[PDB]
Length: 261
Ligand SMILES: Nc1nc(-c2ccc(Cl)c(S(N)(=O)=O)c2)cs1
Ligand SMILES: [Zn+2]
Image (cartoon, rainbow, N blue to C red):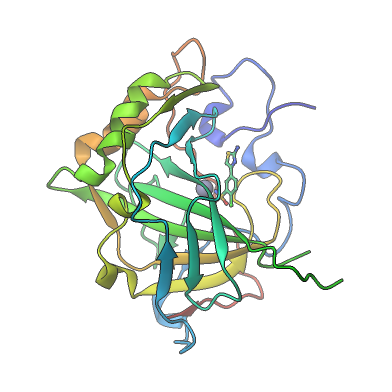
């Protein structure tokens, strides 16, 4: 009756912990995440139009913390999304990442069997209107970006990468230098192509209430920016165990299809 952990991080920690194949909650059901996306097998759906963004361009000073599983920035409902085939507007809650130290294994989703060096999640929750009718398959909207090593610094990512130095231990926080969500995004053309499917959170309690969006095109960071995530973060307060491979094993598609824009 304690923490959960990632496969890698079980043989290094001192509290007892549940490994992925042993996580409880809803983790062991049938509409789980992440998956492999067979790009050819996803039928084009025309209602998957462009996403619209409010608050993404606005400069801000984000609180960012090492929660012992990832590094997370708290977005406090200060940005929002519409479009992308969604039923309603969704308020931005938090953005976090998953990574490895090897280019082929840090992503949670894969595309036609390929895994990327990291994967960025921007977690939104559906807008509470002034109505509500009496297990929502789309309570949460995750925007997901695959990251690969490019040849240049992504200057957009620099206040996040620098703030890594101030939160090495679990339960530490800090404030990033001024920046926008837009700074971390790719240009809008790179945003036109993406995959969609209904799934779960990829960490316990693995609730099956996520409408997923995975953008076909990767973001690029420099190799050394990618590397700062495993070089500066730790899974442990003592700072011996480096935070990496914070990724959930793939889950089966089952009875689901994946569509695309
Ligand atoms: N404290 C922590 N929260 C999460 C979390 C929360 C909500 C979501 Cl939607 C996700 S994920 N990987 O499905 O996008 C992860 C991880 S660690
Ligand atoms: Zn995630």
